[PDB]
Image: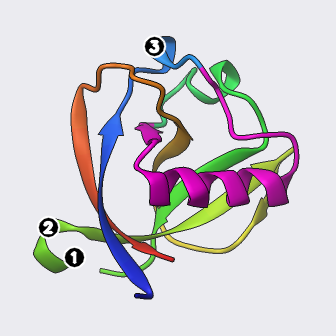
Amino acid sequence: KTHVQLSLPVLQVRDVLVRGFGDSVEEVLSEARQHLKDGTCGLVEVEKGVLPQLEQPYVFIKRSDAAPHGHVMVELVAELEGIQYGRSGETLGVLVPHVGEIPVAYRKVLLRK
């Protein structure tokens, strides 16, 4: 399927144990997609002071369209030293590995895979 319904655990930035997916734009997009498939991906909502507490390159989920079954359609965009790889809509948050942190909420998304 071109899209997959996921419910992403929303994590507090200070709880996150593994603060990124790797060391290159290509690696972080690869790892993010693998963790999204394996159900081991968390979401941090972006506010003032969040991104400096996480590791670059960043992987964002961005709104790809204006929401089937409650699921916002999203795609992945990476960012390294102020350059984004991909073009999409509004940021819903930054993806991180989930290793058992307790979420504050869930974000229903339809991921363009």
11 displayed left or right of 84: left
**Pointers 1 and 2 in contact (C-beta within 8 Å):** yes
> What residue lies at 32% left-to-right and 38% top-to-bottom?
9
Q: Nearer the viewer, mark 3 or mark 1?
A: 3
Q: Residues within 10 Å of mark 1 (few under 14, many from 20)?
A: some
Measure how far apart labels 3 and 1 are at the Cα level: 29 Å
- How many labels sit on residues? 3
Q: Amino acid at mark 2?
A: Gly
Relative image position of residue 75 (x, y in whole percent):
51, 70
Q: Residues within 10 Å of mark 2 (few under 14, many from 20)?
A: few
Q: Residue furthest bottom?
A: 1
Mark earlier in primary sequence (2, 3): 3
For residue 5, side relative to residue 47 (left or right): left
Where residue 113 appears, as percent x and y from the top left, is 51, 77
Q: Residue 30, image x and y in percent?
A: 71, 60
Secondary structure, mark 2, is helix
> What's the CA distance linking mark 2 and mark 3?
27 Å
Residue 91 visible in this rendered orientation of the protein: no
Per the image, label 1 sits on a secondary structure element best described as loop
Image: magenta residue range: 18-45
For label 1, the residue is: 67
Q: Is residue 77 visible?
A: yes
The three-letter code of the residue at mark 1 reads: Ala
Q: Which residue is mark 3?
A: 15
Amino acid at dot 3? Asp
The question of residue 96 being in magenta is answered with no
